Image (tube, rainbow, N blue to C red; front, side, top):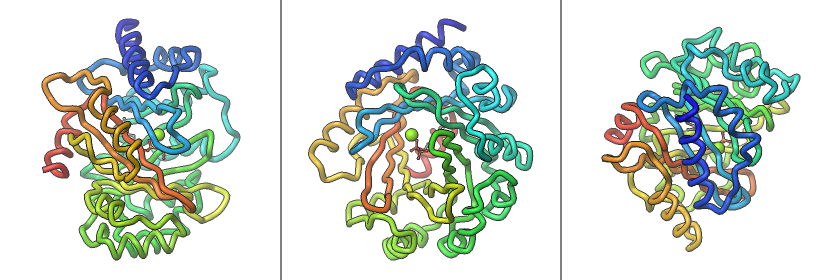
Length: 302
Ligand SMILES: CC(C)=CCC/C(C)=C/COP(=O)(O)OP(=O)(O)O
Ligand SMILES: [Mg+2]
């Protein structure tokens, strides 16, 4: 439906407008048209994410794609929207769906850069572990090489994975996080073992409220590139930053981002990313939600 396409793109321009970013129509429209059938409201999930620091001038968008549509990456490459990288990341999404049960896909891009990643969601009642994922042929070796470290901190079940074709990286979104996993002492030992920025009192408090945690890995080495803690809430003032700018800019976005489910508050997902020499924050404001998001809010934002 050309209608849903225009609408989704307009909302995307709105979100970008809030951060002073311009959408590259030539890179976005073709992508939205290709999966236009998935833009239907109801069972679709769409997110527009902002970030701080060196990411403050970009705006990401995520769109859920039903598995029935087939490998979303093969589609973008076949249509000529993106050039295969020639690396294992090209087959990872396909191999993941082949070896494990995938409940749904998702495409991700940046308003000025275009397409850059896909996601593979797993059934909540049938989530794979570190061992099941590390056995995927195209999966980065780093996953298996860090298996002992993951198990030591209670990172077992994975609710989904994401593949970044431009940076050739993979994220493992751990779920069912225990309390001792998110304890201050545990989080500190973990970051130190990975050589990432040490979170302060404020950051640690945010890590404790996390419902999801995801490390980023690559095919070059067995070293984790960064680690992210995600919190989901309806509260627009949670950005874990002490900078006046961030507090103001994030809260503004959280209260003005577009959303197609009037009648409820905006679902928000905040992120605290720790890299070797710094930390940055991100915030995704959902444009479209489903009962999954509602279920999560009841469980982690009560
Ligand atoms: C359709 C749905 C429900 C999408 C959810 C996407 C999500 C939780 C992304 C987290 O990664 P990121 O956006 O913070 O960045 P990166 O992958 O680059 O680390
Ligand atoms: Mg992003």
